[PDB]
Image (cartoon, coloured by chain):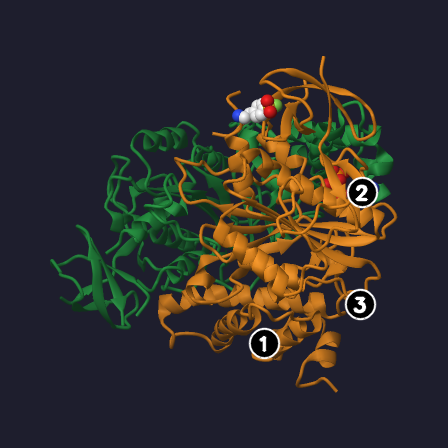
Chain colours: A green, B orange
Amino acid sequence: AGPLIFVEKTEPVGYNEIVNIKMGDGTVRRGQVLDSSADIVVVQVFFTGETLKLPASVDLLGRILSGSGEPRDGGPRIVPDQLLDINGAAMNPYARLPPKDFIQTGISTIDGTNTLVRGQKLPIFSASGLPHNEIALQIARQASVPGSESAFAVVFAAMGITNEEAQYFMSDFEKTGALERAVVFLNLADDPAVERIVTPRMALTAAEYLAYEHGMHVLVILTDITNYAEALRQMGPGYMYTDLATLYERAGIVKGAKGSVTQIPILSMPGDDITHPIPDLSGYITEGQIVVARELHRKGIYPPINVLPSLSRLMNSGIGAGKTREDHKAVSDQMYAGYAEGRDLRGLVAIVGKEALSERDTKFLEFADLFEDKFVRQGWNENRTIEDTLEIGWQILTHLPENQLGRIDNKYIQKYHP
Amino acid sequence: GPLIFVEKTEPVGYNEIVNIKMGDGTVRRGQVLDSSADIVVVQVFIFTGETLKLPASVDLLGRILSGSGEPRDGGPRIVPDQLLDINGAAMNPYARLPPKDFIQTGISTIDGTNTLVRGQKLPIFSASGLPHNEIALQIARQASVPGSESAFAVVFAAMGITNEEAQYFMSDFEKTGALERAVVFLNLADDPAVERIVTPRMALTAAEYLAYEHGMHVLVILTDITNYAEALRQMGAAGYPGYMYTDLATLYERAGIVKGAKGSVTQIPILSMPGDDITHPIPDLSGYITEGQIVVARELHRKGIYPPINVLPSLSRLMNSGIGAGKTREDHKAVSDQMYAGYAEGRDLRGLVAIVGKEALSERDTKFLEFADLFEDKFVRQGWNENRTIEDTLEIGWQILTHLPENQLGRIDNKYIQKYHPAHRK
Ligand SMILES: Nc1ncnc2c1ncn2[C@@H]1O[C@H](COP(=O)(O)OP(=O)(O)OP(=O)(O)O)[C@@H](O)[C@H]1O
Ligand SMILES: NCCc1ccc(S(=O)(=O)F)cc1
């Protein structure tokens, strides 16, 4: 009791009913139904049928499908090279290797201060009426892996999204050209609830197939886990948080260092919380988070990512010499601690006055303006290469006095400072 | 415009212009936004007024008050050696020095894994109906600075609480004994909203007074800052304001080590996400989270574990500053890393078990799964009134790492293993 397996609907079935399943390999399972849809059935292990399966092929990239893997782009049915199982119990393709290499997001708030690393669970922490989806959109079309031998793919999964802003994605993905490396799953709010739950399992497995059996680094974007939750919320329990676990388990470097599975799940605070109680998704926050701040949003900054509450637990693995540029951490640390103080001094100005501040504190204050204005703010079609990211850093690091530059080495300064 | 709290000496009207004498004597302009019975809120852009003053004295510590410094414990008025500005424009007593030494909070999930350092701003991220208020009380009772020659004190601050909770706090703080080190500021939801927003200013001005002028390490606790936002929101006839984010900055400025190093002001604000959202939108309190945050998770509450602090989301940025070798204990960091990873792994394997069954698991994988179970049970779970010393905290960490095999213990130096692992420890 506890787990779930998603099975093909061969016959109409009831509730709490004894039935059989023909697994991906074989191991026959004793289970009971929980809920049903039109083609999919959920069964808790501990008539005769078989698991719902994903048509795994390199022909998945370039095509758009629904949560159950049904086509949406008007095109044909996906021709399956293999017939893999949804819940990632097929190969067990992950290694006992720590996430190491670097992935470029294009956004400097991430790439600079909270670097994303090949195989990481870096969620975006957000709320309603915030541009999180449009950040995820920007990642999908701008993401790449500078240097790596392996091809790069993106798996974009949407859950509980409305028609009007479903066409948003459909248009964006095609009119950018970044479809030819991206498998896109869409799940409508109007779509069956059981189809929502299976969506990320279809998304992750598609990436697992690609990363392992075609040795490529794959980045998965799950837009709003909260919406995944509200479908599970309504499903009718002692699986509440362990189900979440089965989703954040599927992250890291695959067997044979060539490929990778990386995640950016969006977690956002709901429209209503009392009538629809939202679980703490804190289980997903283990390798850091990317905080989106309403404060930066209200002063007209995109992307409104507050770097301070944000971090990447594995950044130090994917930065510096060879991976990026050796002065990466040197700049990051300085930019962080720099912006950190300038921001706190913004309180000190309100207390004592603009004309009562130290000249030291004023150049720190103004730095916080510059960081938000010139570094944090980038266009929606601005794909800042890691060099620029670091360079824009240096440009604003010139404003604060040199003898106040935190802990950097002279060699890092004298060479890379204008 | 930024709001300044003014001593009511004269009747005032809305939008009227005033000239406030400062803590030193630099007269400044502004206009009236709102007022209480005896306090006036003024935004800086003929009448001259004085700033609100705190009845500052060593003679505090023991008495409970209102957010205006008005006695609640039936005792006398506070006899002030000096009445200094509450807006912080009295001293600026903070030094250009990074928070260093350690604070014994008594809780493992904080002390061990997310160590609290003197002068830090480490919030407790919570939600509706979580034990956050209980954690605060436990910290207040237990907190200490071992070894440190500076006298330790705790300043407690309540915003928009209820009478039930007011009796919960007052009663505890008295009988537990932690009052002869505590200045308690209590403000309940029926005390004018004007006094609610002044409450943290008072608490911080008391903290600033003790730390600087009396060589003190002071710990400030602001309970539920989402209620403070609620008072900011519903302010005057003149969705959240513009000065809202800027106003919080006047609070999270006031923390750190005092001039001359002989004292500090440490900050534990409570940030709890509310019930509704279309009514009461959630504020961007991310202005506070800069030096880490402590996360209390429902998952652990629902399983019946106090304190329900999840260490994986939790963090302290400046932990390294007050930990190990005559600070806590040399091994400390080598234990934290190994516990964190061992819990992170286990936590993951609670999923893999639901994918391929309990039996269909690896030998090593089963051990980390069981570790993740022991972590919550014996390292996370601690009594409401047990003050675990760092030595205890870490030795518990050793009694838990024994369950894991030695060849898997990697985030730790071997010179630490042969010295401290119960199977070796000669
Ligand atoms: N001279 C300095 N060089 C580099 N970093 C410094 C210096 N002085 C302070 N800092 C940084 O500032 C932080 C001090 O924390 P504290 O909360 O006391 O100040 P703050 O609120 O960041 O800034 P302020 O008090 O000026 O508004 C430390 O994390 C430290 O790294
Ligand atoms: N709504 C109460 C606001 C208020 C309260 C008191 C005054 S005063 O006349 O006493 F100065 C003025 C305005």
Question: Eyeballing the image, is A69 above or below B250?
Answer: below
Mark 2 beta carbon near ligand 1 (under 8 Å): yes
| Amino acid type, label 1 | Ile
Disc 1 CB within 8 Å of nearest ligand 1 atom: no
Q: Is residue A106 visible?
A: yes
Where residue A398 sits: x, y (%)?
Answer: 79, 30
Out of B162 and B312, give the one closest to the viewer: B162
Q: Quadrant of the C terminus of chain B?
A: bottom right
Mark closest to the chain's N terminus, 2 or 1: 2
Estimate the spatial distance between the alpha carbons at disc 2 and disc 3, rounded to whole Å: 27 Å
Which residue in the protein does label 2 denote?
B94
| A208 relative to B411, above or below | above
* Picture coordinates of residue B43, whole percent (x, y): 65, 23
Where residue B108 appears, as percent x and y from the top left, is: 62, 66
Chain identity of mark 3: B
Identify which residue is drawn at 76% across, 69% down: B330
Work out whether A359 lies above or below A42.
above
Amino acid found under the numbered disc labelled 3 = Ala
Q: CA distance from mark 2 to mark 1?
A: 41 Å
Residue to which mark 3 is pinned: B325
- The residue beneath circle 1 is B400
Same chain check for tags 2 and 1: yes
Where ligand 2 lies, by quadrant? top right
Left-right relation of B241 to A66: right
Element under label 2?
loop
Q: Residue at x 78, y 43 (%)?
A: B80
